[PDB]
Image: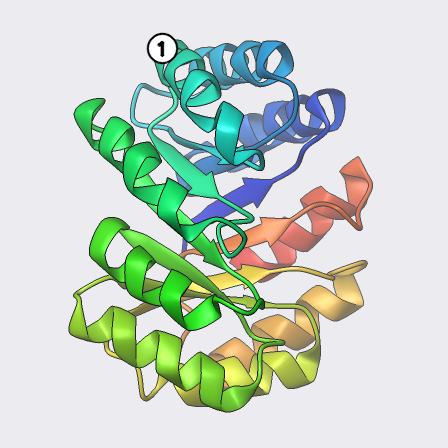
Amino acid sequence: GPGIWLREVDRDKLIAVAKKLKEIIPDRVKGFVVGGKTDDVVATIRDLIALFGPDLEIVVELTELDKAIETMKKAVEAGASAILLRDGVRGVEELRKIAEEAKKLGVKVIVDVTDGPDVLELAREAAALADAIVIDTGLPLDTREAIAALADAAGVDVIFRVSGLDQVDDAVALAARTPAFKGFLLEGVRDVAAAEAVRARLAAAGLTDLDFLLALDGLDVDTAIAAALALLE
């Protein structure tokens, strides 16, 4: 079956969810995407590594390009294994240095590709630097096809960020055209009913077994667990 990644920026909420997942479905938990203050993220990373095994992957979100390397070094020292660079479309020339320092640490590089004047240049740079690219499905279709074709040719894993059910249909169709496609980042799930609709669409597309990420932004602890279990059944 598929494995679950969880994205949550609140430490108290993430740990409460993580403790429950460890008790119920520890072997299905693949990793966590964490963010926030360096002091909070580093404490979360240690807590998550204490809960789960040394095999737990932890992605630290970097939202400030000029502070990314310092936050990355401290997070990796806590046990993080990957970075997710957001806001790269503003200053594309800054990603090489960040990606170079990530590589020197043996850290995976994930680049979030969102809209902007330099979105194609960001996509090109991400293709030359990143292990994986997260493509916002809300992007215009021709732009998304461009980014996916660029990443595929570079051998970069492609992750589709989806929020609407129509975004799911878009990403599913494009996923079948993208060999580099690796999985979905599920945003907007607010109850088990929405989690069921996604699970059914993924089943109809034959994409169930791929690991996915569930963003917990729109969920409380009990609904996050119920939505996670609903997607994983």
Q: Position of residue 43 (x, y in %)?
A: 57, 9
From this viewpoint, is residue 185 visible? Answer: yes
Q: Quadrant of the C terminus?
A: bottom right
Which amino acid lies under the numbered mark 1 shown in the image of this protein? Glu
Q: Position of residue 172 (x, y in %)?
A: 47, 83
Number of callouts: 1
From the viewer's perspective, tell me whether residue 219 is left or right of residue 51: right
SS assignment at label 1: helix
Instruction: Identify the residue shown where x is 52% and y is 52%.
Output: 213
Residue under label 1: 77
Q: Position of residue 138 (x, y in %)?
A: 63, 76
- Between 206 and 43, the one nearer to me in the picture: 43
From this viewpoint, is residue 206 visible? Answer: no
In the displayed structure, would residue 62 be above or below residue 41? Answer: below
Instruction: Identify the residue shown where x is 66% and y is 85%.
Output: 166
Q: Position of residue 26 (x, y in %)?
A: 46, 32
- Between 71 and 43, the one nearer to me in the picture: 71
Q: Quadrant of the N terminus?
A: bottom left
